[PDB]
């Protein structure tokens, strides 16, 4: 002994698995390597893609010397908030016409989820009620648990969702978990392109889900991270949110522009709030301002400026919808091709889930022991859950992946 | 029959944050003599925002570089930004940098850096999940300091004496007494330079006395550094206190903002610098910071951090930036000197050396609330009830009117 560090007992936090997987993919010398663990759009040449419309808008911003760097309002750039909420709800939304919608610019979809969770933990179902159950899908994006736990919720639960046998939605289990949820429980719902499985309810299934939630006063907290990106069409991909609005729900929707604009690193999100009346929006927003203030003070400008300009200009909007469909069509192509080649190899089991699923992520139905084969033997990198990113498939590796998967079903 | 009440029906309306209505009232005022001394950011002599020339230049270079992509940054942020930011605060020759016992977390402005640090301390400092460690802020401080530490879960927020109303300066004896009486391990939120809102800073000799009590009572320094370079034009002088604490062997946090010294307010550029006793703890601390960031904003934005990293890493841009910072610092120094000279030429009662002894864009003038009300209502000069002014609200054109009006308030009111 000779003063002790105030950090002497701080533990090393747990190694998250996906980041070491992409690291292990990079260490691999094998020239057959394929990374199906990526979590962002990639071209047929395995490259990131800045959207043409984004490049165009970035040039217009750079050429506009009148733009300053003064703080945005706490709740964000007004034109961005309006355009983002209109994108989710539709231009002609009655909720917008009736002035009962609010929008809070946020730091990606994550920031929107966090602001909403903080609000609910303080002002929903009582004051400072940390006991309201929060239900997330089984499985879901793992940061869902972390966000709601950090907001103080003590009772995080899951609803049945992925059926490992049918390779699809366990609707009966989901409905039963809704029926058994205490009234006023919060449900975190993927608006489309469920992450990580890719399996979405059909509109008819959504109507059954909404019916139970309406009867039991369950709160819909939608996450919309893939609007337009998922199917190629922004209107189709927002239908479930808009259906809940038309059924009279009050709800939150955490929107991300990370994927559909490719603006991952500019942290562009929006929390849309739908209430019964305009006065409630004013009071809710006043509390969300306090929450934002003590978290990031006010939000950054560059990404929200890009989105606002694109969505406000019909010519740019049309160009953007084309760029979005290009991404969705490449994914739809990889799904169609993978299924066709797996069926051409006569691979055991059914494979229609590969094309029934929606978005960039797919639960393939492979088991962990089959996963380790693809990694160790064939250098195809994917998660133990069997999740793949379809953007890791290309015209050049599709045959290798499909044959390796066929070997990974018949031999292992 | 009756529609159910909204699930939001009992949510109260929050009450506004004071200065926003003041600015709104200024904007609606028809009088051509009106002056906004309540502004919270740098303004030119023509009352305008100023994008720094070096920032415009780097933005053009970024826009012309098609190789840059938009893929997620690491959770902790852009590596070159974090290294450059911590080196700016600590100095290239810092013993802590040489010994590899420094971490840096890119954050959403200085506010985000304060919040990440507060969340970490509320989980891992002075025990596990100890929400009872006292957190001390200056009397007065930026009110969002209290809100950040309260939201991180600290239940015992206290203040240390700081502004002396009678002397128009630092209450050193009160500050030292509050340090001496603070429970061991209490956290002190310290303004590294250009105290906000008063402009009153300890001298180096006073900082040595403050540090001596903190060392002896094991009090944790959580510095804010929002005005480095902006305050004096001299980056080393403006970081002297942080560097002195490092030299004295403290572990500390430093929440840095680039909102003011780069004028990058709306790009939300900050960095939390961590100084630890031993290099091996930095990896452990940063691993916990990663978890905190992940559930807050996931990962930080690129644009502003790229601008700062490019400027600080290139000799030619760095030199241009230091000149741009000096331009801002010198304008504020000029407004302070000119205001003091006019108040003394008018033989205004009281002492006015605090107008030039204070540092940075904010000044506690010493005017009382009734005098402030006179300035707003009678003279259309807008400032806060505390008597805080922003020196950037003064201009060559308005200085005579502002000084004359202050002289009127002092002699006629109260």
Image (spheres, coloured by chain):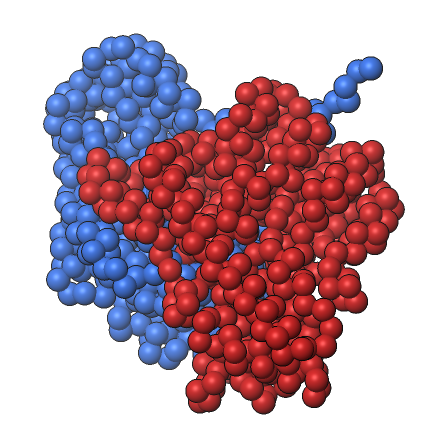
Chain colours: A red, B blue
Residue B307 visible (yes or no) = yes
Q: Position of residue A275 (x, y in %)?
A: 64, 27
Q: Is residue B404 above or below residue B356?
A: above
Q: Residue furthest front?
A: A344
Relative to residue B224, is residue A144 drawn left or right? right
Say which quadrant the N terminus of chain A sits in.
Answer: bottom right
Q: Position of residue B291 (x, y in %)?
A: 57, 63
- Where does residue B307 sit, x and y in percent of width and height? 27, 56
Which residue corresponds to the image point at 19% horizontal and 52% vertical from the top-left?
B60
Query: B393 or A276, which is in the foreground?
Result: A276
Q: Where in the figure is residue B93, as x and y percent of width and height?
A: 26, 73
Q: Quadrant of residue B50?
A: top left
Residue plotted at (36% across, 23% down): B23
Q: Nearer the viewer, residue A239 or B206?
A: A239
Residue at screen point 77% across, 63% down: A166
- Tell me where residue B368 sits by quadrant: top left
């Amino acid at each position: 002994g000779m003063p002790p560090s105030v950090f002497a007992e701080v533990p090393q936090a747990q190694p998250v698995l996906v980041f070491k997987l992409i690291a292990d993919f990079r260490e691999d010398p094998d020239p057959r390597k394929v990374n199906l663990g990526v979590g962002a759009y990639r071209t047929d040449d395995c490259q990131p893609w800045v959207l043409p419309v984004v490049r165009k808008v970035e040039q217009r911003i750079a050429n506009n010397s009148s733009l300053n760097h003064e703080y945005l309002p706490i709740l964000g750039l007004a034109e961005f908030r309006t355009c983002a909420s209109r994108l989710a709800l539709g231009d002609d939304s009655p909720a917008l016409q009736e002035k009962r919608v609010g929008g809070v610019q946020s730091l990606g979809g994550t920031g929107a989820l966090r602001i909403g969770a903080e609000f609910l933990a303080r002002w929903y179902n009582g004051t400072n009620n940390k006991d309201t159950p929060v239900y997330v899908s089984s499985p879901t994006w793992e940061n869902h648990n972390g966000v709601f736990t950090t907001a103080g919720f003590k009772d995080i639960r899951s609803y049945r969702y992925w059926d490992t046998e049918k390779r699809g939605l366990d609707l009966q289990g989901f409905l039963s978990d809704l029926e058994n949820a205490p009234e006023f429980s919060i449900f975190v719902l993927h608006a489309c392109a469920h992450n990580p499985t890719g399996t979405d309810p059909t509109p008819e299934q959504w109507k059954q889900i909404a019916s139970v939630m309406k009867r039991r006063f369950l709160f819909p907290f939608f996450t919309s991270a893939y609007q337009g990106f998922a199917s190629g069409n922004l209107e189709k991909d927002a239908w479930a949110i808009r259906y809940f609005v038309s059924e009279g729900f009050e709800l939150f929707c955490a929107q991300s522009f990370s994927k559909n604009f490719g603006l991952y690193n500019e942290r562009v999100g929006n929390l849309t709030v739908v209430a019964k009346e305009p006065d409630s929006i004013l009071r809710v927003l006043s509390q969300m301002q306090k929450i934002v203030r003590v978290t990031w003070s006010n939000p950054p400008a560059q990404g929200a400026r890009i989105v606002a300009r694109t969505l406000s200009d019909p010519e740019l909007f049309h160009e953007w919808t084309g760029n979005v469909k290009t991404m969705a069509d490449r994914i739809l192509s990889m799904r169609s091709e993978l299924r066709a080649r797996l069926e051409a190899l006569k691979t055991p089991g059914t494979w229609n889930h590969i094309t029934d699923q929606i978005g960039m992520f797919s639960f393939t139905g492979l088991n962990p022991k089959q996963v380790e084969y693809l990694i160790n033997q064939k250098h195809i990198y994917l998660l133990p859950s069997g999740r793949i990113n379809m953007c890791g498939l290309t015209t050049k590796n599709l045959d290798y992946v499909a044959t390796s998967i066929h070997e990974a079903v018949t031999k292992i």
